[PDB]
Length: 356
Ligand SMILES: Cc1ccc(C(=O)NC2CC2)cc1-c1ccc2nc(NCCN3CCOCC3)ncc2c1
Image 1: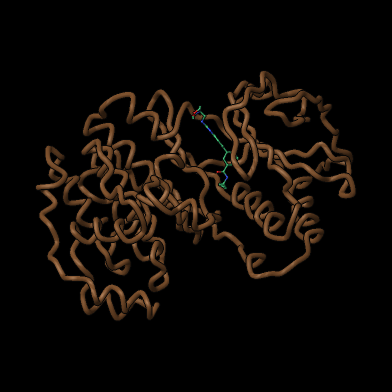
Image 2: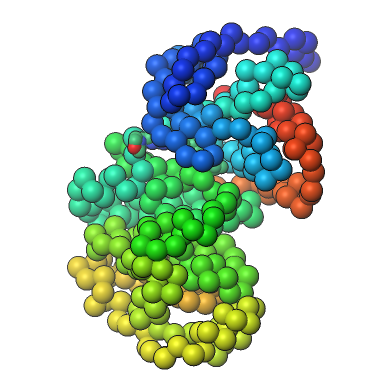
């Protein structure tokens, strides 16, 4: 039968990077800072053990408060669960600490991608075929992420990573941790989200993500941001001018009272002609967009339905658009202390088995 009686502890080494100390296993070499954020820093490196170029994220003060602690656990679980080509997955996760008492840091190793969707667009114009392959993968990814009952909630170009051969992976899904002041004003952060989730209407389903995919594809085709609004309200108006104002049907389904109340007061207007906005676009694309850009979430196309759309005919392969196992998110409805979230996280680290 054979069992592993004793696991060997790799030998780490320190070095200062990004004004912060990075202690990692000697397998990872040539660490170079590629970014930062309020969640932790990121370094590109070379994994001599696998010959792969990898991305390493060092969370910053992962257990400094219940809110942080729980999120640190949440991220580890999300990464551990995803195992699909178009979704960022966990290649390794380590901590220099030798025991739960010492435990303070968490490093998450993932694949490395040449760039995010922003960078690419600025570099050149993409062919109708490029858009097809690019959007096709986002949908393959979402199909998989959604099947494990997980919603992204914040899909946008900065979350989509691609590389030289046009291959894409989805990042930062299921995290939904943003303070309202970064989503205020003329900011690209709030230009790709569904109106329902932006102005907190009814509840939202997986289709919030399909609306985002709509805004991205529109952009890749036209070369311009579809709804570049200056604030939540201006943003909503730009959207309504194109898709039209709510209708009795969807209006009743809007759970929020103040919201429902404000929508009513808006002067009404019909759905514009999509062929006149996304011009010079493959006609099949225009059709897919009219099925992605619908105000009512109950009537928005799903990722699996969309893979079946004639536009992705050259890439659609049902015998190769995998689904995930269900994600067990019961922990999400718990209220534990920092040390309890930490302990759970610690367990998830020493129990991680490297992919084949
Ligand atoms: C490590 C990690 C851990 C976790 C998660 C994550 O999503 N967790 C959520 C799902 C649960 C993501 C990463 C991660 C982070 C940044 C990345 N950046 C690049 N692009 C670098 C090239 N650039 C482009 C911009 O300009 C400079 C150069 N490639 C791959 C990356 C992988």
